[PDB]
Image 1 (cartoon, rainbow over the protein chains, first blue to last red):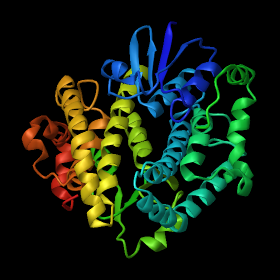
Image 2: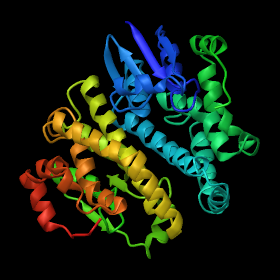
Image 3: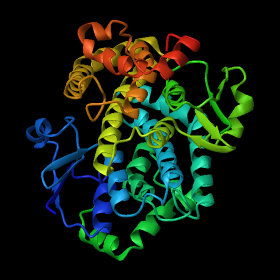
Image 4: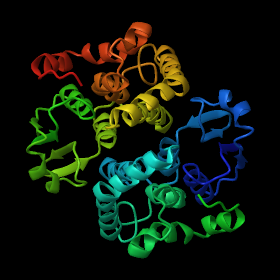
Length: 203
Length: 203
């Protein structure tokens, strides 16, 4: 099909979709829209946001919704409602981690950002990290179901971005399990090829 | 089945599940756990969070994931992947609105909360509200697909909470469309009965 994916020239919350497209054997136009050009695209998107995946002219917006859909299409969303649910559930938990880091990262006032970071370091981060370590361990290096799912692509795509907002480059040094969903995804020849083939960014 | 739902004694992000249970004709123990008792339940939940829906002893956590599952079970998630996707997508957009209001509401420092509120009033809120008004209008008073979906229950459950965090009690005075998904959900005899039957809270 003619597939066009529009996002910023970073990984952040759109790279999971690219990864899933590479996985499915879908060729697509990787339209990386810079911040400078974004204003001309914005009004042509469903929500005034990216990512937007367009397939034969139909637009799909919202990163998690697009990932679950590609996952469903590519056999990566479990084999019944209860398995699909587990993936949704664990990905919704990852979302809590991202939202928590993002409350700190997008704080423009340095002194307030510092107090928020200290608060989270004592009150949410330790618990998030232990819980994520439990989940990856229980699931043998995966986000859900003990095996490859679209939730691994969600995690793999946004992992560096999470680390950058956490200001925690060494995160997987305390928690080596944290690298594993990325290894699972990069194990797939089609995906590894796309990655070698794709631009690099620090988030 | 034996169904037990655990959440705080408010509507906030758990009431959509109660509404969906009432919809499906599911009797359940509405376990409203107060803030004072929550610490004894916390370690018995999958993520150290509520809501948790328990069915024949299996635990389901994470509010949006639980709603999509109940929706799927009750025929409210569209009739194919593309329709299900639309519901996911629009609900993910509502989530952006809630996350934006919540960045203001949970700010403990009054002066910082004021500056954030002013910023959002000029830079995100007007756009969110127009976009939500477009969606409800396009969908004839519903969140998705032009008809009743689990996304209407998501919205109905959390609407007062959203308004309280927006500090905008009159919100649907500018935007009368905003009341409509609540009317659609309360139109259902089984649901209206539960509501008349249920406790009231301001969020």
